[PDB]
Length: 155
Length: 155
Image (tube, rainbow over all chains, first blue to last red):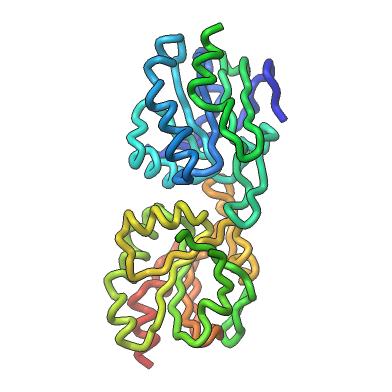
C-alpha cells in the first residue's frame, strides 16, 4: 500500500474526450484525488462526489489546482456518471482494469458485486508526491470526504 | 466455451430492486439473452440494446417469454443504464465479477479498457437449455442483434 511521501506509480488513467500518465497530469500542481468503489453507487453518487462538487471552489481557494475522482470503471461509465452528477469542476479518471489501484495497493475484492474495485480514499498530491493519504475504514465514510480534506488544507 | 444443447451453469445474476439463480429465473420459459461488453458503451447503447427494445413485442409475438441483457457490470450501473435507455421491456442482469461469463467460457480481456468483460453474444434458451448461440466475431456486430435472433425464431 502506498504511503505519504512517495511519488505515485508511473501508471495511466483514461478519460473520454486519452491515457493520462498521472506523473505528467499531476506535475506542478496541488491535486486532490479521491477514489470511489464504483460509479453510480449510492454513497459515491449521494455523498462522496457531491461533497467535492459543493466544496470545489473552497478547495481551490485554499490552493488546490485540480480535483480528480478515480474509479475502477471504464471511461464511458465515468463520463456518463459525471454528466448525471453535473461534475463539471471534477476530473473523472478511469482505472478500468484496476492497474493504477493495484499499483497503489489500494484495491479491494467486492466479489460478486463488481470484482476488484478501489478502496475509498482521498489524497493531497503536491507535484506528484503524496502529501496526505486518507483511507477509509471498511464500509465507512469519514476521512475521505471533502470536508476532511478541506480541514487538512487548513494546517 | 458453452455450446448449444447444454444447460446453463448454475450461477447467479444480480438485479437491483436479488441474486437470481439463472436455472430458476429461466425455467419454463423461452428466453432471449444477449450480452454486451459494457453498459454505456457506444455499440451497446446505440445499436445492440436499442435493437432489442424496438423488436421486443415482435420477439414476444414469436413465443419469447423473457428478453434479458447481461453485462460484466455491477447492478447499480445496469439499473442506471436501463433507465437512461428506457429499457422497460428488457431485464438487465449484472455479472459484476464475470463469474457467470467465465463459467460460460465467453469472457474476453479488454485489458486497460475495463478488464475482463463479456464477449458479445445472443442466445435462445428453452427451459434452461441453450437452443441457439450466436457469438460475435471480434469487434463485430452481425449475429447477436435482435434482427438475427428474430430470423432464428422464423424457423
